[PDB]
Image: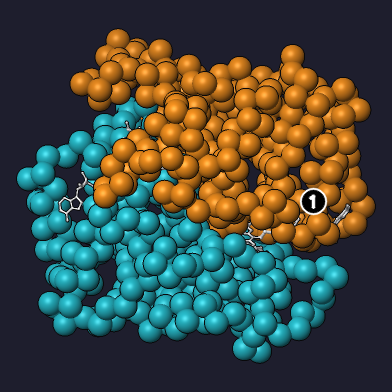
Chain colours: A orange, B cyan
Amino acid sequence: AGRRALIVLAHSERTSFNYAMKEAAAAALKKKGWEVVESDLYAMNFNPIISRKDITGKLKDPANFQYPAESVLAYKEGHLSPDIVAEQKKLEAADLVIFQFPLQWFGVPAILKGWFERVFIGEFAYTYAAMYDKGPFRSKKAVLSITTGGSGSMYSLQGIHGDMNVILWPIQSGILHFCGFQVLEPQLTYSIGHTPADARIQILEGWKKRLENIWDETPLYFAPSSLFDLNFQAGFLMKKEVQDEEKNKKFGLSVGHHLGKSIPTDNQIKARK
Amino acid sequence: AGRRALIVLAHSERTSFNYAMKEAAAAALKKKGWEVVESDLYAMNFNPIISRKDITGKLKDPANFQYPAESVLAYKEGHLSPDIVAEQKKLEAADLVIFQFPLQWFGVPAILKGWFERVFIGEFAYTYAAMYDKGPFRSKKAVLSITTGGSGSMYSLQGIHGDMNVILWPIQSGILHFCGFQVLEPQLTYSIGHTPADARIQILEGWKKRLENIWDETPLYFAPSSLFDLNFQAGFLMKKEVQDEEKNKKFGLSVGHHLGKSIPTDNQIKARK
Ligand SMILES: Cc1cc2nc3c(=O)[nH]c(=O)nc-3n(C[C@H](O)[C@H](O)[C@H](O)COP(=O)(O)OP(=O)(O)OC[C@H]3O[C@@H](n4cnc5c(N)ncnc54)[C@H](O)[C@@H]3O)c2cc1C
Ligand SMILES: Cc1cc2nc3c(=O)[nH]c(=O)nc-3n(C[C@H](O)[C@H](O)[C@H](O)COP(=O)(O)OP(=O)(O)OC[C@H]3O[C@@H](n4cnc5c(N)ncnc54)[C@H](O)[C@@H]3O)c2cc1C
Ligand SMILES: CC1=C(N2CC2)C(=O)C(CO)=C(N2CC2)C1=O
Ligand SMILES: CC1=C(N2CC2)C(=O)C(CO)=C(N2CC2)C1=O
């Protein structure tokens, strides 16, 4: 299973429900014997802005700075900024990674987005030669615990905001799975600002309850890489054999791989697929 | 038509293609007689982290700080920090707003995410009473000019990254359209790191000629608010008549309002509603 957990929190107030959720998670995991490390970005006064100062040594081409290549080279030679390296060390150590944050402008808070940009460096977090399920974090599991202002109905198929599954995709598939993470069902707590005091108590208890058997959960479904032609000249498109077999299927494979068909229900919210 | 434009750029290097794109757009728009103002976030030494430091007066509740409520009060009473006030003034004046940036982890750079969070304050940028269609910026138009590392095929319905339309949804509908903006087709330039010197010159020229008639363009299609019951009681769900009349249609209304059916082709990439 997993003995180590890393909890990344993105909220400035320790009086917030998000802070309470992080505390609940840490407590529940420690009771079950987990090793729990934290990355409270606001408390760490974490720098979320990507720049050449993320590289400590001499750049290869200082007059024409390219973040991707320079950062990769710094990773391999050992000269990434030390604050970045400390986070990478936490990730390598962790089996389970929990991201706690309030939904902000239908995405991750700026400080967490900057954490991904600075910490998920090439080679370390991903490889074009081993994308998605064969990525570096393929033996790890990630989970998003989100709080929101809008009610759950606003995010249903017929709500004004639209399907929450669409909002989740860029993060869960694009950021987490691309690196190899097995992504578990998200913990969604809607309109927390309009939730009764006693209901709020249950929310915290239900979260701690779920974490007791978190590692045994079945992850969300993403189309396996074995279905794609993993080479540049082919354009990373689905292999024809697969493409044809799918032509008689009613449903697409996932949110991003809907193929023009119907997206299976709650592909990004519920496992089993 | 419009005569005032605001270009928000999110890239640290003046030697980048994004910078070139911003220079191109500014040049063309001025030629056509527009008033062009710029927000080079990196050069502005812009702080993308929301906090109580965004309010200069006294908080109504210093013990339990809640950003939404406090920032709105700050806007009403005139206590927002100097940098937020200055960007709000640029936005208030602008007819067209261009967001130029490199795609980073399937979204906008952290520094630009932070810009929306600190600038797009309630009452000023949005009201729950007048969401989407009837928002404050309903008389304005916005466009995304994005550069990527991966090729277009990777972002096709059969590409390994999945459909680009799902990636654009949370930004175009969730941030821009929510405040009332009419969103024009995104300018998408894929695999800019593998494009021949000659082709790149063509991209700059193509972008410039598009900006000459940009205002007369047909905006992207988003389901109107008239199709929903805009009240907390109704949960902001789609109207009954609407739902039933929609059950006879093959395609959903948009990426977010796919209704479990097929997503209309390039809903977030091409107009024609
Ligand atoms: C810039 C910005 C953009 C946003 N964009 C969006 C968006 O796109 N979509 C959207 O839906 N929402 C959006 N929101 C709203 C945001 O998602 C919610 O305000 C947030 O999730 C509310 O949770 P909270 O923990 O931050 O804080 P709080 O508002 O503090 O609420 C937690 C509640 O639980 C209580 N509480 C605290 N600790 C405990 C405890 N231990 N036990 C029991 N009760 C407790 C508190 O008193 C309070 O009533 C945005 C907010 C901001 C500031
Ligand atoms: C943290 C991070 C996350 C990323 N996540 C993703 C992702 O999720 N998906 C993805 O697809 N990509 C991703 N990328 C890649 C990124 O999108 C590309 O590296 C970026 O879009 C390349 O454009 P550029 O303008 O930054 O710079 P450059 O790579 O410099 O390229 C511009 C090119 O045009 C040339 N040029 C410059 N000025 C001019 C001019 N005036 N005329 C003609 N030619 C000119 C340059 O010499 C260069 O070859 C990520 C990158 C980072 C750093
Ligand atoms: C979308 C959305 C918000 N984001 C900023 C725009 C928001 O702040 C709140 C309230 O915290 C919402 N709930 C009242 C319904 C909401 O739906
Ligand atoms: C997804 C993705 C990237 N983001 C950072 C993870 C990236 O940087 C590049 C670089 O140009 C890609 N292209 C090679 C195919 C890519 O596909």
The image quadrant that residue B148 belongs to is: top left
Q: Tell me where residue B268 appears, x and y as whole percent.
A: 35, 50
Decide if residue A193 is on the left or right side of residue B152.
Answer: right
The amino acid on which the numbered mark 1 sits, given as a three-letter code, is: Tyr
The chain to which mark 1 is attached is A
Which quadrant does the C terminus of chain A fall into? Answer: top right
Residue shown at 49% from the left, 27% from the top: A124
In the displayed orientation, state which residue is furthest to the left: B198
Ligand 1 within 8 angstroms of badge 1 C-beta: yes
In the displayed orientation, state which residue is furthest to the front: A58
Q: Tell me where residue A201 appears, x and y as whole percent.
A: 90, 48
Residue shown at 87% from the left, 29% from the top: A30
Q: Is residue A24 in view from this perspective?
A: yes
Residue shown at 58% from the left, 40% from the top: A82
Task: Tell me the SS state at disc 1.
Answer: helix
Image quadrant of ligand 2? top left
Residue shown at 79% from the left, 44% from the top: A22
Decide if residue B121 is on the left or right side of residue A35.
Answer: left
Q: In this view, does A269 lie above or below B22?
A: above
Residue under numbered circle 1: A19
